Amino acid sequence: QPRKKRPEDFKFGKILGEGSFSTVVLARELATSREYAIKILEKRHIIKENKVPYVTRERDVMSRLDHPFFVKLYFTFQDDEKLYFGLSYAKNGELLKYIRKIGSFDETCTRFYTAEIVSALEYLHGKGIIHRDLKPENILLNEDMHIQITDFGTAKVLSSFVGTAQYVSPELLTEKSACKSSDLWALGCIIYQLVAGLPPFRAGNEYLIFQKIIKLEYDFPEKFFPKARDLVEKLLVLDATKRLGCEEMEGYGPLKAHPFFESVTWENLHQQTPPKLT
Ligand SMILES: CC(C)n1cc(C(=O)c2cncc(N[C@@H]3COC[C@@H]3c3ccc(F)cc3)n2)c2c(N)ncnc21
């Protein structure tokens, strides 16, 4: 093992973002010039808020992932007050940024990024890991414009937590259980948001959004790519055992074979040149 890193090994730079229990800061390792996104978590706050399980799971899940469509965890260390996780620096930021910037994706762009997401979910589910809070804010983009999915402290590892309201699956509201097919529901919402520019269930507060989700209350705009609409319809299904991609629907084969993805080559997407946005 390389020796444990420590804060004095880095020149810390700008804050990349701030969350409830952590802050992500750009850092340059002095010995190498390499840049990392270092997530910094204060131990007292985690302990006080009973978040030890989530921080431990984040580290344990990330250390298991070895795939190009996920943020990598390179190292961890801690001082008296703080934990530090050394992550890949995804230089192009959140997918959410591009959706806002561009408005909505054309069909080529929608299909390519949707295929990367499906391919990442196939890998994650194959290891028995459910993300449980998938959304455009934690699907990051590297400097080559491939995805890197992050934000694993809320993940479930298969042998309590409700995600961002827009992407919450009806089973979490109707019987508090999560399964692989909950991530496929979020996938449906994300595909919808790429094409439409907005997520499918929106309202002025969380209670109202939850009410639309359990009623399957959303509509497609007139413009929506027909094969993408057909795919979203087969993912936003109330019954979690009937979503394309789930085990009871015979898994990722039938999803990857959906007509929306006809021209996709699945085997080497990360070596393909992404289509330019917009
Ligand atoms: C875009 C920027 C902020 N950013 C984030 C990166 C992470 O890895 C990461 C890790 N855990 C969660 C998370 N996002 C969570 C989803 O919604 C908000 C919440 C949140 C939570 C804490 C926080 F501090 C910022 C955002 N992101 C990253 C990176 N690796 N490389 C380049 N930039 C990066």
Image (cartoon, rainbow, N blue to C red):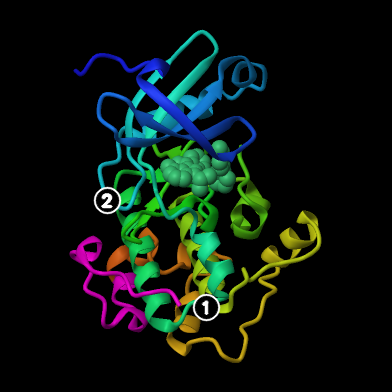
Q: Position of residue 58 (x, y in %)?
A: 44, 32
In percent of the image, x 57 and y 75: which residue is there? 103
Quadrant position of residue 77? top left
Question: Circle 1: is it few (<14), some (14-19), or many (20+) Cα within 10 Å?
Answer: many
Magenta region: which residues?
254-278
* Amino acid type, residue under disc 1 in the picture: Val
Q: Amino acid at mark 2?
A: Pro
Q: Does the magenta segment cover residue 264?
A: yes
Chief secondary structure of the magenta span?
loop
Q: Is residue 159 left or right of residue 219?
A: left
Q: Residue at x 64, y 34 (%)?
A: 20
Label 2 sits on residue: 68
Dividing the picture into quarters, in which one does residue 222 lie?
Answer: bottom right
Q: Position of residue 158 (x, y in %)?
A: 40, 39
Horizontally, residue 212 falls left or right of residue 172, namely: right
The tag on residue 235 is: none
Residue 47 visible to an observer of this rendering = yes
Q: Which residue is more in the foreground, 245 or 209?
A: 209
Give the answer, above or below, for where 166 lies relative to 107.
Answer: above
Front-most of residues 67 and 230:
67
Residue at label 1? 195
